[PDB]
Image (tube, rainbow over the protein chains, first blue to last red):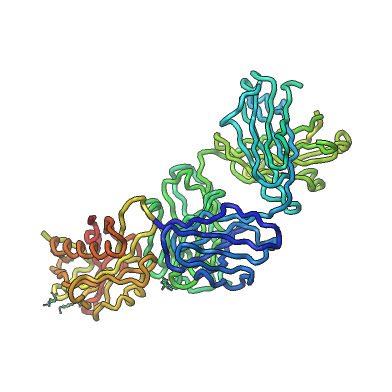
Length: 209
Length: 218
Length: 169
Ligand SMILES: *[C@@H]1O[C@H](CO)[C@@H](O)[C@H](O)[C@H]1NC(C)=O
Ligand SMILES: *[C@@H]1O[C@H](CO)[C@@H](O)[C@H](O)[C@H]1NC(C)=O
Ligand SMILES: *[C@@H]1O[C@H](CO)[C@@H](O)[C@H](O)[C@H]1NC(C)=O
């Protein structure tokens, strides 16, 4: 079983700079390797074949190289359309993919918390939303504390794609509880740990206030 | 120009079977191998097998052997992919790809992809709940909670397109109940609360549900 | 004991031939096990023609009255790691297939087993000391999913399902 390993999993590159994507094969393989680009919502587009040959119409800034167990895709100068997911391929086996994202200055998240609406409480379910707005990089830690008790297995996080204008991320963590469990406790808080915050930020509220 | 056009998206109950089409044009259909590649939501590309359109011979990946059948109709230049006894693991976008030359693995041509959702859930409209602002500097955040709908997608707009800056509509998440849910949020000046009305416009085409919810402070 | 292959229509006794070679497709993917699976070739006439071990007989899945190897079985391929490329198998001593004329052709079970054992040994050489498995055709048009050949202006289709049902270590 031949395994293609791409590194890094995510590549953060400042706009206009050079990017180097790696692709390592578990065992030595022939120099028959292809690189694909996939923008969200689209099928993959072939970039390189034969480990160094550009497909028709592919801009000159894309170049391929490698031999044996190491293969490299190089973009000489990143452009706006170049930020996507890249896959290397050898015969039937694909790589897990490397995402090239825009690298910008650190931006601290703005943290908000939303108590469940009374209309939703009528249905027997309660959802608490913690919002992280316009932060970079994507790595963030969000924890739920209900009466100082850490929550586990009852929250889901959603992350937007990098913003088309300021290249930031936004994240929502939703805590889902029954109406019976929601009214057993008073104080609900989310703790947000991000590189752009000197100390973690906590947003909290008292139920009914 | 050479292109591959696939069949539309389908939603299937677990244990059933689905057939996906791939019609080829502007090239000799029998001269190039047709491969099928599937991509789970957010995950990588997985090769399922190829079919020789000239002879109808097939070579399936050992994972899919006994679950996948590949055929073609040379008269209409269409390649078919059938998966049987569907599972939630089989929810993915299924692509048909064509080799650059006879039997190459350089996929220079792809279909637009067919999405297959395997779920026991039935069509259900969303319930929209407010995310009211309360009490970050001079900026206030509010939004709408769109919960318990199936299937995707759901569109959200604010003030019928009048309010666009600062709007973030998060990708849907699949809950344990088999129903999708998402939120849309917007940051607005705190002074505008109580003088500017904020309404989120939620549409769910599969259920023909259209909800206009006003978000009010406190 | 003989292996009986259903054929349609009935091949006359004078169409009995010598099996001198095979063409195979190695199945793609992996099973997290030390097994390699081979099937009758899923390709077309292009795969058969490029083997260059065929005689005047036009045949599929089996070379009839073709070239024989000198000492031992020889397997060839343009790329062993490309499962889209068929593997040409050239026997050293042929295996006779006898068509009675009643709609079935017969093959010696013991003689066919020994040849498969030799092929699996040569296949292990190219793919490591692994289990070699033969499985029936993955499917296709009747002339390729079956073993087909021409003889005296007629075309015959023989089901080769029993010819690939063995596992070798
Ligand atoms: C076989 O693989 C080699 C590399 O090992 C490649 O150069 C050659 O083109 C391949 N032959 C084909 C695809 O027919
Ligand atoms: C193969 O050779 C034998 C012996 O010469 C001949 O009788 C037979 O017809 C040949 N097979 C075919 C399919 O022509
Ligand atoms: C097969 O080869 C043998 C010699 O090895 C030859 O005598 C015979 O005619 C050939 N054909 C058949 C159908 O046995």
